[PDB]
Image 1 (cartoon, helix red, strand yellow):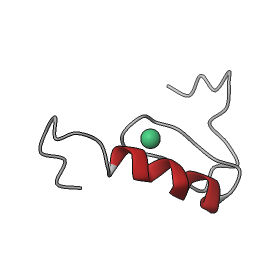
Image 2 (cartoon, protein in one colour; image 1 turned 180 degrees about the vertical axis):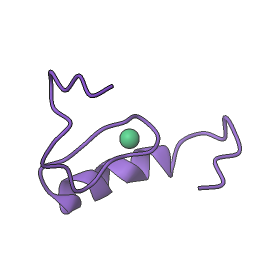
Image 3 (tube, protein in one colour; image 1 turned 45 degrees about the vertical axis):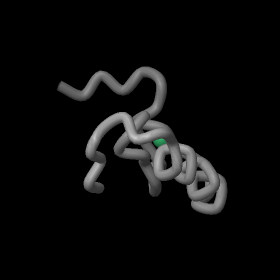
Image 4 (cartoon, protein in one colour; image 1 turned 120 degrees about the horizontal axis):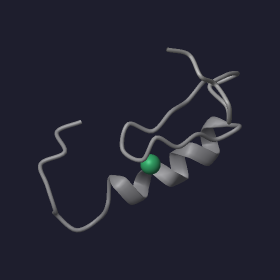
Length: 46
Ligand SMILES: [Zn+2]
């Protein structure tokens, strides 16, 4: 079921932690650190 209302297009990079996107990679990268640098809550094993 494709109900693309908000986005779901022109995507190149997506975070498999908070389903976030960034027009560019660099932007996403700096955002990844957060998920890959936060208190040990659970075994990410990404
Ligand atoms: Zn994220």
